[PDB]
Length: 626
Ligand SMILES: CCCCCC/C=C\CCCCCCCCCC(=O)OC[C@H](COP(=O)(O)OCCN)OC(=O)CCC/C=C/CCCCCCCC
Ligand SMILES: [Fe+2]
Ligand code: NA
Image (tube, rainbow, N blue to C red; front, side):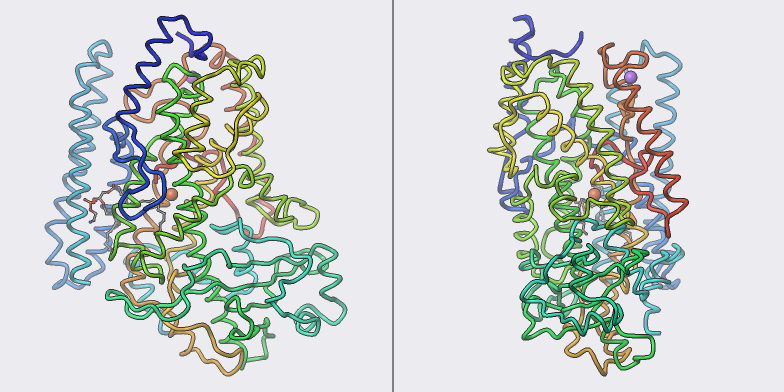
């Protein structure tokens, strides 16, 4: 039976669907008092049907067990004894659980008619792998209870290969390239006049870029780009923050200027101010290779920027603006769009695992003494409130990719050619938009169908009200609905992938990036030494948690954008409506467009300085689930 808008449903349908929604509202419940994320709309609890499926669980547990094995194997024999039996047990039990799944799948194939009798056993296996994860939790607690000068930062990897950044992190061009191809491609903006509190002069600029260049000429020819971390607020504490587990830590809200050469061959760092106030933060100017008395001050200044970057990327770009936005849309959808509504059918796959993983963020990562309290310099209460505040301030329309690019004046490939996130992101954004347009056109023939849809009206009301999604507004027509759906889907799939999956290759090595420093910002551009820079490096506990959590979060690829097939047993099609699924129809056209996009990105990557692969559709999950 094809999905329908409520106004066109037969009365049998209208009462069935309305009672189903009444039932949903008792199961999916809003709260703004969820532990460790106060003020952010969350599910009060994760319903049984929102627990992760066995496929996700086996994949996630597999990575976690690899990490445990790797950690135990890195220890000396005396220390390993405490954990070897427990690790061998988890490993063996995971393998047994894989075999139960494989036997169940073979059993279902041998008699599909009788496959309905297996559902309690599939849920039993779900319960079992979750219980295995609870045992991991206890083991992690025990490990933490027993917790060139950079050897310790290689040691925490065990036998995992160090990422490429471990070799290249001191390079100026690599540092600049993070701004357009790194985990946070959203902050960089064109600058036309410098902020008043960033007093970089013409002479300093020419010192770096040459006597025949100038600030005026660079600005006017669209060659100046600024990173300004002012929005970090309390994520950049005033001074020292002392904590039990990690001792004394610092973080920062710096300002950095980047410039293209006249040939636009690549972005270069020009100057860094390590805080917002120039009276207390001197200007650091990119040194020449011969200026050994400026070298270490500059390394320290870049490290200040990278400290700011992990804070901004992880709390705002990753947690606040993907995970915590998709939380609200998941809830609104389940509470207000009936399962027989075509938009429920379309959107539900894009929220698979979202409630579960976000509850995990709040319960595991955000409490006092948890991962974020260790890895991020600010007091945990400030981290929670600042990340929460960023989620509440995030404007849904202004946050749309095209709008973001235009507002930052980075949307013109002629002015800023090497910006992989922009170029690949637009291909994916536009493919999703055409899909949303085709799908909306099946079910909505007029703007009247949009405004007379009482469920959609209620959905918008919940997104604005209980969901606290800033910038969201009444939906009065088909074009607008298409833009909204494009943003919801892109946010859940591609945006998350772009900022989540760089974690293993770019964020696992603490000297290249860390959300806390063990020393204040460099007090002077000149006279610094390697020892002064090493003092910024965090304690080893920070590095240990970092390598493991960031490897995990970027190693689970579950589901795929455009596949629209269940990701757990029985793996059935998401759509039944032949108007959607027909040969050459909307879904097939979307799937085909995604393959063209993939081919285009692969061609672009042959010509790029380094491949950018995070927005390859084959590497984009449909939902935010890790
Ligand atoms: C950090 C910034 C991220 C921001 C974005 C957050 C977005 C959402 C991501 C949320 C992710 C939530 C955390 C992952 C969720 C994994 C799926 C899951 O739900 O797992 C549940 C288990 C058990 O939970 P429970 O409450 O019983 O006990 C926790 C400890 N008190 O949690 C873990 O395995 C610990 C994982 C920590 C990582 C261990 C890595 C291997 C360690 C082995 C080597 C030991 C080294 C210490
Ligand atoms: Fe994530
Ligand atoms: Na299909």
